[PDB]
Image (cartoon, coloured by chain):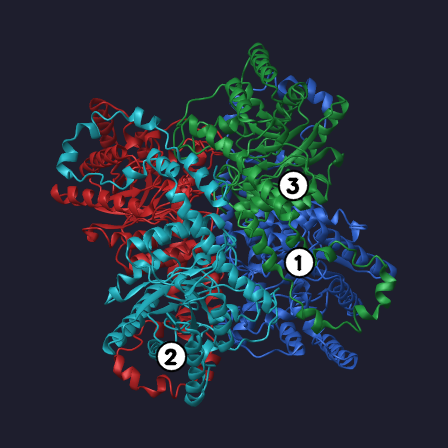
Chain colours: A blue, B green, C red, D cyan
Amino acid sequence: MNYQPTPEDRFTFGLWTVGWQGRDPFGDATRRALDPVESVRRLAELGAHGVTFHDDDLIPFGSSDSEREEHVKRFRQALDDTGMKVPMATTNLFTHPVFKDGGFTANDRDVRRYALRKTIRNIDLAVELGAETYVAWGGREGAESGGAKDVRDALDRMKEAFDLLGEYVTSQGYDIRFAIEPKPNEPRGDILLPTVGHALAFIERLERPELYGVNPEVGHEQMAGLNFPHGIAQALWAGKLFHIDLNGQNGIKYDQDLRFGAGDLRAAFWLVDLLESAGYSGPRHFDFKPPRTEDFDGVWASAAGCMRNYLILKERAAAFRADPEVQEALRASRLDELARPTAADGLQALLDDRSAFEEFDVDAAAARGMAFERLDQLAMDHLLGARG
Amino acid sequence: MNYQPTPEDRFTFGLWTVGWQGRDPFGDATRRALDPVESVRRLAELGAHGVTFHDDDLIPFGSSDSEREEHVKRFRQALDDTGMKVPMATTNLFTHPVFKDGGFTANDRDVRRYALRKTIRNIDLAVELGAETYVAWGGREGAESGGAKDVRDALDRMKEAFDLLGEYVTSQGYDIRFAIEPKPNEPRGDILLPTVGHALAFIERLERPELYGVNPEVGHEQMAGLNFPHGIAQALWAGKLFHIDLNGQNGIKYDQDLRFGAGDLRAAFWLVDLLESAGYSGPRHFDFKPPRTEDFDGVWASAAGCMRNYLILKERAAAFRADPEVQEALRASRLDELARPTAADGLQALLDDRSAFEEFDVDAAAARGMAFERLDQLAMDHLLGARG
Amino acid sequence: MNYQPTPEDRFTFGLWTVGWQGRDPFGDATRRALDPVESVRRLAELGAHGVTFHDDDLIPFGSSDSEREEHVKRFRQALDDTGMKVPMATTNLFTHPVFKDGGFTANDRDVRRYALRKTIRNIDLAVELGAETYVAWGGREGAESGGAKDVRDALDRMKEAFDLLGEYVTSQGYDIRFAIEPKPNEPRGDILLPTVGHALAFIERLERPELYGVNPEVGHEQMAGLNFPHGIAQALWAGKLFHIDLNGQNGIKYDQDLRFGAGDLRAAFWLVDLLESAGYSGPRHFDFKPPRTEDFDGVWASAAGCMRNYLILKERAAAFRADPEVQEALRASRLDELARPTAADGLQALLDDRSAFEEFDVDAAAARGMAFERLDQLAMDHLLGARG
Amino acid sequence: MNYQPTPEDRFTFGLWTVGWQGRDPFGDATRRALDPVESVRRLAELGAHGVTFHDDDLIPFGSSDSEREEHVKRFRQALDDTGMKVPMATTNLFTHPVFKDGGFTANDRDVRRYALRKTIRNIDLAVELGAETYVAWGGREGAESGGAKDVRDALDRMKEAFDLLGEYVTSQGYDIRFAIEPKPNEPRGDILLPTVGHALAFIERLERPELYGVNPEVGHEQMAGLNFPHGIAQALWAGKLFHIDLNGQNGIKYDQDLRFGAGDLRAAFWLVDLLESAGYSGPRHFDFKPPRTEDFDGVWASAAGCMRNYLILKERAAAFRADPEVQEALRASRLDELARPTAADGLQALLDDRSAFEEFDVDAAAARGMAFERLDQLAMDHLLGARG
């Protein structure tokens, strides 16, 4: 009947999401700032499993090591009092004007070195707070113009940065992995490693590829008009889905960061189906923004909404896969045959198989309908709770 | 002054481009069919270096082995008479209704086997005609609905197909490589391996990755709103640019297949800059369609146009890179620093470097302008021939 | 419980939708042709209220007046036997190669005259069959290049065409209205009057604007990334929604023509909400294509699907508006205040109103939250049938 | 040879463009604020004809009437010292949190009244400074969710607002016209009157339509994937192009506000061709942002760039239209026939014209090629300065 989250649902939220003040490129903040401790408490009450942070969300940029220890201890006490976990952390390499041309791939070499020292410092902090995943979103790595960035040199510099972080973590004996987060654009004209695919290909060029995976985001792939569930399947196929960011997006436009379930609802349905079917066991992280039209009550309603919509879709997709009429339709559409090897008999047997070519009745094959529309209307009926 | 192509320019054209009859989803053919021999002759006269083909462009589907030999011999004679080469060939796995749910990843296993036998047969033909690159465009590999295709099983089947083709080629001792051609959509709702990135990541999972690269297409990446020169740089960085398809596209919409230079002209400029700077030496292949508004004279004007616009951009980009004021602006924007290692001194030296963090003047760094707009206006002036 | 359509639901289908053979730009037909009589019969059995046609769907292009009368009489008998109506008809001005540069705005003046005579002929036929709406979709009116079409002269020619059709209809005393159907692109690079807005503005320039409205299509506005329910509201506001075409589209790409409810499901929900709330009483027309993966059984399943998804959304939107908790949330979000005049007191009273400016507490106003997220989660819960 | 602007070129700039501090949704300001007086002086030195402003650019929000008079007098002195004009002004109804749900169409009625009083106040100021055009950009008029805004009530409120402003201006005897500026999205999920078309249709519903036109922006129509030159032609056709905003945009994504000429260079070429050919005589206004990567030197280089690229395109388009080979190609493509009435002979003569139908040789018509590709390559050659 109802859809109450529990910390066993592994729902997590960034400090920066519910704490977004409402500043957009055309307007002033509409909400006062939130204390991180307050967020941890409110989220805990909503059923969340944990929070995530950028270094600058937790410790104001240019804090003395004294202020730093103080900010951390307060945070830690909030975690102890609530049972909230910190499964992921990340570095802000995009807000300060020093990162206007990027962090790891800034043309200025001294900014690149600074970016790495800022990162390493927060990796230590994240390990201490017990994070298992360290996310890297190269929001400023890119260009507005063709001549401003030689992309092969920038990829050299990016690989250099990630290889050095991999060296550091292995030298420290830390138990933490990296997840690269792609985005095609905004705030840069074009961002490097713009999609899950580009990030997966890149990783295979690092010195220790086993240390790195992807942190795809719903809205980000959709800003390229791509099919998010398909891209997630490729990441799963590659064994690289280390984390995931959930939100909603209405097509190709600025990054809207709507609550999860908003935006493309059928894509959310197929995403949940796949995560649950594949046994993804990492956090279900929400990287979203309550619209600036909202007051704090609207903020917590929006965050509750994220979790509620995941649990409703989870139920509907489970119902869909458990439905015997659906299982018969999957066989009718030959999903079972898709899962069988094309040619386990091997190359030579295939070459000698006259039924595969010389004697293949192509006209009869062509006439078989795939029965996909009936299957899809079953999926729709299950999504809408109209099964009868 | 003028811009005449020579076969040394390695400009190539698919039989299907100038031979497109003008059939689109809303309308009948506006042009009669072209004989392949006629195309080879006309293109040779225009300065082209070679042609490419799908098996079905050259031998009508369901031709007897007798008709087949006949079609090939005619073709071959045309090549001998003109000096035209065949550097690339590919398989049509998308036109016949038997491929309505795909070739290599069709749900029906017997269609998948047939698709592989059709492919292998044309690989032999391509080696004979001396092609060095075999292209695979999985135009029908994908779905219109979420339940119709389990994407992890489909990627298993795709890897299976490509691994078997790799086995075949190595067993035959052939000197030919594969290039996968991505496209995000059309004619399927969503196509598997939708961008260069996804194709690069995929290849790294094949049994013999060294046999496979990418054949990116301008219009295709732009249908995802992606930056084509950036994606090409990543392919070059990976050492995987085996071939390239040139055309024009006006943004995110149906695949327009405009002549090269049409569409996004600045992107074409930066693409040519990169190909010539990186020393890409493969064919410059045009995969485009003369608009159906045109008669055959318009067809050859459109094909001449492709080559002419490449040679004009080539000249302008060479002029841009040779310009001492541009070389000074690149230094002003610190492109030289981008090419230098961030930390050749290594991790420990970086960790002990107080100028990289403790003593880094972040406020002075932040105040340095990147001077990118002046550089870009220099690039614009060079493109428009307005340098003074 | 279930969702059975009746002819009172005014669901209509074009002959060309269920009769689409599956030819797309990359592939051959996958289905044999359907006899119009068979379609009328099958659709009648599915609960449809009527059918629509292009002149060329019903009478093969270049039919003798004898064949013509024969085709019509057969059709008519099918309508009599089933009770099916013909509420709308339209002209095919896009398939024949003579229309490759358009019909009403072709550069060649003799093609423009021919286009008008072909149109007028079918208007007579449509009046005879009792249609009340005549649709004009200028699918070929546009350009692939900047110089090919002077758009001001083309708009002159378009207005000329529509004014002449308006003269004809009034001179014949016919009781029929025109609906212009916009589309931003495909099959032309850019099509004239690309959105509902452009078509509405245009109409206001015709000699008898009262004779013309719009026939917006879901997928078409979404190919421009526009909000279809918003555009429909503007048409309703203007009193110009004469007809509507329903289907599904997954974002900005080629025109997918998916069954209604597929594509952007939340947009379909808000569209149905608005049509039913505004009391739109015209046909609910489906302009869609069963995917070419399907056989004829899949064809009729896809058409049934269109009607079923409308009736499910209709129920959910009615439930949403009837819900007292929703009506309280609408008041909380001040939808009631939106409907009240800003200044029924008039200009001078507003100018003398110190509470509107001098004494307006802007800081308190700014702090009121809009409560939109709670309202939207109520809408989501109602859509998913999760209200508790 | 070179391309120096003069105030006779009527190039204008908003205070907010060169004065943009570099704050984007992901980052802090990278540049200090500019004094309006300094901007007027620097722009005057660059050859600009005038500046424009939002009320809040010139007088800080919540300034005492004393501070106000002071800010204005300083501004005025700068204008007197430089000869700079103020042809357009506008209201900021989007930055202050009180406008988070819009100005003219905010759900809260007291915000709507406040929005109108803020507007009226600046209209007086603009008339005083001698502006001839008052621009309205409803940046916050829209919604992120379906239920938050009844679009028919919002259009009622929008018409109410504009009718009241029209009453005010006529009652004051002011010589000023309004230009509505459409944008499809950002910062709202969807914005009302999202394209030029929707704004043109809307105006026709106002009480005094003659007082209102459009202020289209390059990047805005391109964010909908629309053809900007086509939309501008429709506005010209309607006699409603009162002002225009020039900038550059790379496709469908966030509003990039690149300098003019950047983005889609061929579209800029065809836009300049049309403005100059149609005799548009209003300001050429640049609404753009120097990238935040830039220091103040980059700011002025970027602004110089806008004007330079217009003057280069102006020259190339003039050269194109003056070229006798182009004029012959226009005749070959029958642009001359497009400009002739389809049927000046009238309806009855057309109906009795057997050459228009009964005896029209459709097959010969269909075979005529349009010769559009040759024409377009001539346009390309002229744009690139490669004519020989």
Q: Secondary structure at mark 3?
A: helix
Q: Nearer the viewer, residue D320 or A95?
A: D320
Q: Which mark is residue C60?
A: none
- The answer to whether residue A22 shows anywhere in this view is yes
Task: Decide: is C78 above or below C333.
Answer: above
Q: How much space separates mark 3 and mark 1, taking CA atoms?
A: 22 Å
Q: Nearer the viewer, residue B260 or D312?
A: D312
Question: Residue under mark 3: which chain is it in?
Answer: B
Question: Residue under mark 2: which chain is it in?
Answer: D
Amino acid at pointer 3: Leu
Q: Which of labels 2 and 3 is toward the front?
A: 3
Amino acid at pointer 1: Glu
Task: Decide: is C188 above or below C355.
Answer: above
Outermost top residue: B66
- The answer to whether residue A385 shows anywhere in this view is no
Q: How much space separates mark 2 and mark 3, taking CA atoms?
A: 55 Å
Q: Which residue is mark 2?
A: D118
Q: Secondary structure at mark 2?
A: helix
Q: Which mark is residue B275?
A: 3
Q: Which of labels 3 and 1 is toward the front?
A: 3
Quarter of the image for residue D169 reads bottom left
Label 1 neighbour load within 10 Å: few <14, some 14-19, many 20+: many
Q: How much space separates mark 1 and mark 2, taking CA atoms?
A: 41 Å
Q: Is residue A110 left or right of residue B50?
A: right
